[PDB]
Image 1 (cartoon, rainbow over the protein chains, first blue to last red):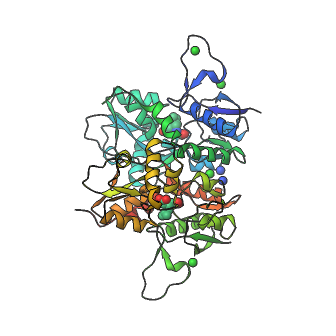
Image 2: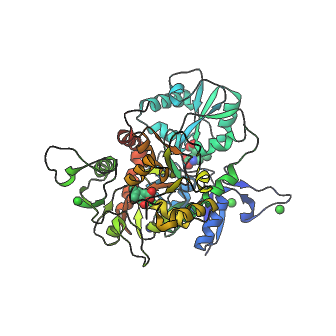
Image 3: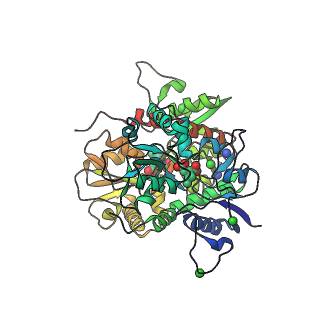
Length: 254
Length: 254
Ligand SMILES: C=C(C)[C@H]1CN[C@H](C(=O)O)[C@H]1CC(=O)O
Ligand SMILES: C=C(C)[C@H]1CN[C@H](C(=O)O)[C@H]1CC(=O)O
Ligand SMILES: [Cl-]
Ligand SMILES: [Cl-]
Ligand SMILES: [Cl-]
Ligand SMILES: [Cl-]
Ligand SMILES: [N+]
Ligand SMILES: [N+]
């Protein structure tokens, strides 16, 4: 039987394909994660239906501690796999079973080119430049939970004024960096994609932490360890590197 | 419960402590992996007994498909955990379980500063500068199995002439780089440790691949998932970063 795969639109992982006619089914989509799912299905021999997560969220807890997003789909057995840039975090790994990482990344800073700002510390010790993150994503959660001095300071700033420095999604954050005096705390793999495409933006500093994206499965899933092995195969054969180059390469920026 | 932990001496992961008198039991050792044990044991509650792997190997297969080293200890249920720089690989994942990674690295090149060599391709396209890897380690296995043309070329060279370009262990490789015209293919975290301590040596190029070290367990072990959760906790709190900095930082280079 066919596996149900929950996912979410996010460039260049999952995108609607361009066509002159309405699209249906898996043919609606392309991107890094679709290529990954193709290669996993060729190794393991499953068929799959891709289904966008109905609430359009990744996965976080409400005040009752109930989950939402892709994470909740897995928990409730409404999906067999989640294939998306879903960050492997302590809070999520308690409730679902992630494969080992297919991509390795960290939080970093997206900002304008040409400025004296060089680090998170540089941001934290001032108030003129605004800075934030996507609300309720793993980056925000990192700042909220940190007991490291600099990151707390930054959290105090981000959460101030009813979280006015936060944004609902990455595209809103990018447009805010492009238009106003604002820096976005963003996952490094997304910064790499953005800066290959808008030449006035750059990454500031290095990575603030280290983590991965993994395929999500419900706790107890027999597919988890099989997908880990298939990922390690694809990594060792250079295929994951090829897939990243295909989807990230931009040809217009210095 | 007291867990039995298999490990191997490897700087700065597991080292004999310095003392005026003979040392006994866990008190014989210090290093990044001993610190990681103390943190995992604090989180999860277990006691532990560290025992060096009797054959002094990590774990590779022979012709008959038989395993040795720490991997074979876990397969045979002679240890509960392997805590070491044990690379998470496709072949080992088929026979043991691993936690998610506590460190993320890739193969790169250790060579002398101030030469024209800038990449693996530079090494592959010539025969004058010798290059190789630790025999039967995961780096050697990477080259042996690769179908990427550059890496196939490299493997043909390393394996030529009775594997004269390979070395038995990392310290042998580092002495050969320091004395002769030789480059060592080495995991990037060990290169960082070496270059902090040998100011004439450097990493050449970037990482050739991406992989992690994980705690090994027998297949089916209930500790594997508990240790993963504990590692994610330590990562997000910045403790793994602090541990790396403690063991890696050297006295400075001119
Ligand atoms: C695109 C966003 C909302 C996702 C992607 N990975 C993170 C997650 O899985 O929580 C979120 C990004 C962030 O928090 O910077
Ligand atoms: C120190 C050595 C022999 C180990 C460490 N990790 C690799 C392993 O787990 O196979 C080996 C290194 C390498 O192959 O470059
Ligand atoms: Cl078409
Ligand atoms: Cl859908
Ligand atoms: Cl895992
Ligand atoms: Cl021992
Ligand atoms: N899990
Ligand atoms: N496994």
